[PDB]
Length: 225
Ligand SMILES: [Ca+2]
Figure 1: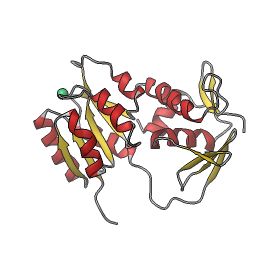
Figure 2 (figure 1 turned 60 degrees about the vertical axis):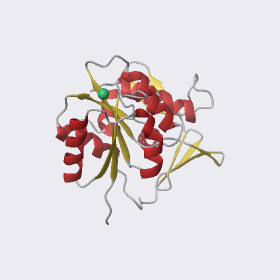
Figure 3 (figure 1 turned 90 degrees about the vertical axis):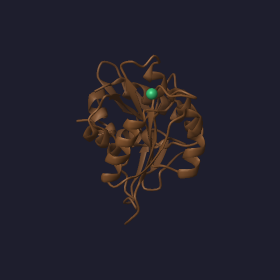
């Protein structure tokens, strides 16, 4: 009810971009394509896509750079497309805020699964208030606060914190978090990277966490509320 979600494809491989256009539209998405990193900020602001698929190695400005630019602008989900030939490290992209990455060549069904995993949130979510350590979360309002002041988080950082806060006594391994938050049915550094990005925003002192705790040897868990 009733409008199509919109994906921006940022890739200079015009054949793959054409195929992605065809596959995504048959799945019910609207799509647009650009072929140069220098066009991305204007494209995102003009189209407001629900998600961006982003080639790591691009003309004009590479994918790590595009990331940093778009993340200064919004939390819009970004999935990096990587290839074994890439000459730059996809981890710098994740550290800059890319939510996820998929290796070329990929099957279009796995690509579509990655897209849908980032777009699971309903409109009009049921009422739900959580707390974790000294942080409050109003889930359907997408608002995290400490002493009433809001803490800004990307949707991925928000989903990570909510999963810990919902089960404050649970220790989550990294594979368990990948599957639960990222939605896989492989790379657990994704979890490490985004934990650090989340801590950098919600911790009074990120070197000494109270909100998101490391359980050495096992995983992570909610701080003592
Ligand atoms: Ca490329």
